[PDB]
Amino acid sequence: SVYTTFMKSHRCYDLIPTSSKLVVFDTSLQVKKAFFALVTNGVRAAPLWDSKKQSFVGMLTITDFINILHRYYKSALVQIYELEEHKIETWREVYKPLVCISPNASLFDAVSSLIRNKIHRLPVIDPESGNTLYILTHKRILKFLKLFITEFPKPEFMSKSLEELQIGTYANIAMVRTTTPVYVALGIFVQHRVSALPVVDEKGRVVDIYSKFDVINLAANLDVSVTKALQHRSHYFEGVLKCYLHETLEAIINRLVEAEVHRLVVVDEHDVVKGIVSLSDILQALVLT
Amino acid sequence: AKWHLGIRSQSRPNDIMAEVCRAIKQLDYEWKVVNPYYLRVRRKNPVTSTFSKMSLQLYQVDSRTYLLDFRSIDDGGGGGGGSHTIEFFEMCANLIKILA
Amino acid sequence: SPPILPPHLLQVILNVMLNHLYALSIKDSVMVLSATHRYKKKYVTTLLYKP
Ligand SMILES: Nc1ncnc2c1ncn2[C@@H]1O[C@H](COP(=O)(O)O)[C@@H](O)[C@H]1O
Ligand SMILES: Nc1ncnc2c1ncn2[C@@H]1O[C@H](COP(=O)(O)O)[C@@H](O)[C@H]1O
Ligand SMILES: Nc1ncnc2c1ncn2[C@@H]1O[C@H](COP(=O)(O)O)[C@@H](O)[C@H]1O
């Protein structure tokens, strides 16, 4: 496949922006300052540095912040308030080896690494200097593939509809209602290990979307409704980006890249959610052709 | 956020270079005096056994104020499974600590 | 007497400087250090949060 050949012939280095910022936490850092540093810097993940061992040992991402908030909320109900002054190392102890990639590794290896390990963050680490150079994402990769692959030769499957390809998830879709408390959302996130939740109504029609990303805004209150929390919507919002089963892989990939979101909600004529199509599904389907 | 370059002092330039040699000697780093106001300092990582190098340069920014500048040297240093960059930060942090 | 600061070597940054150490005013016993480095033609500014 053209995608497969392109991925194998390009290095991870080629994906790195000319200029970027990286946020690193010493594992002795207190968890509460760690998550305030993510927000302030507008970053979604941070490599962890163990000073005693003199090396990176893991990642701190929004998923962890959510695990910790959820734990904090429950514990509080039982008068346990320890997560506050917790160091990162101590909270890691309470409970996933570092997975990284060399800038000289192929794009194919990067993609396989994300899928196999079920992660969303892949630090590019130079084996020579030992420095983390950049954190690779599904989003960055797909955009790059779309930009740098010629439209033709075009694989036949790119013209196939979602219906035919069966890419994405179409059963047991974790969803919340507009009247759903933020703390209930956290529990669903933690249980289902899913990057976002469609917000539906009485009849099951999607009207909004609640992402793991929309949660960290809260480290800069867990009682408010999902709807109410999605009013501090920092970015201009045109409504929920969706797709239909009749649509081609090509149109869906184009929509994803242009909108720069991690997933579309598959929906029927009535805006009723039928499934989810995520960059995770897309990249996987492309790496297995 | 407000970022500051290196560290400032209002002591005499000679006095400043004195304190930094002492801070260096305390951490047990190696150092070479290029200029009276320019030092290269080397250090072997206790864990990774690799070496890291950096420059210490004193500048005058005021009539009464001086600025000690830290620069990492890209000499193929660090990389022991460590990080040249992070290890640079730690050498500096330690020095800045001993001062103050 | 020491050399005068080079004009492009900025003393303060608000939100040739390559490899130079920058830092925030210490607060809460946490130190934040920063610097921009180069890997071939790619530049990254690393911030380290250290107690
Ligand atoms: N590159 C990585 N290496 C090791 N662990 C990771 C990596 N990326 C994410 N994780 C962890 O895996 C879990 C899922 O994170 P995420 O993929 O960001 O939703 C979180 O607990 C992360 O801390
Ligand atoms: N709200 C959801 N409910 C059920 N499955 C989902 C949901 N969101 C994503 N998935 C699936 O979980 C896998 C990882 O997607 P993501 O969490 O978006 O990286 C993909 O196969 C998605 O189709
Ligand atoms: N399918 C979608 N439709 C509309 N907005 C979305 C969609 N997916 C994510 N977002 C928003 O885009 C931002 C980035 O989320 P993510 O795509 O998870 O990185 C979040 O604020 C989401 O609420």
Image: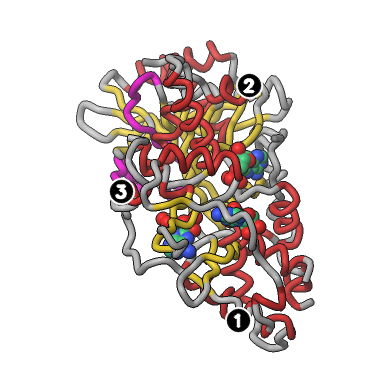
Q: Mark 2, residues whose alpha carbon is within 10 Å: few (<14), some, or many (≥20)?
A: few
- Left or right: residue A9 versus residue A79 is right
Q: Mark 3, residues whose alpha carbon is within 10 Å: few (<14), some, or many (≥20)?
A: some
Placement of A86 over or under A106, stated as above or below: above
Per the image, the residue denoted by label 2 is: A93
Per the image, the residue denoted by label 1 is: A246
User: Mark 3 falls on what kind of element?
Assistant: helix
Q: Quadrant where the N terminus of chain A lies?
A: bottom right
Q: Quadrant of residue A283?
A: bottom right
The residue under the point 41% across, 20% down is B17
Asked if the residue at tag 3 contacts the one at tag 1, i.e. Cβ–Cβ closer than 8 Å, the answer is no
Could you tell me which chain the residue with mark 3 belongs to? Answer: A
Per the image, the residue denoted by label 3 is: A228
The front one of A187 and B14 is: A187
Q: Quadrant where the C terminus of chain A lies?
A: bottom right
**In terms of sequence position, does the residue under pointer 1 or pointer 3 come before the other?**
3
Query: Given this view, does label 2 or label 1 mark the residue nearer the observer?
Result: 1
The front one of A6 and A211 is: A211
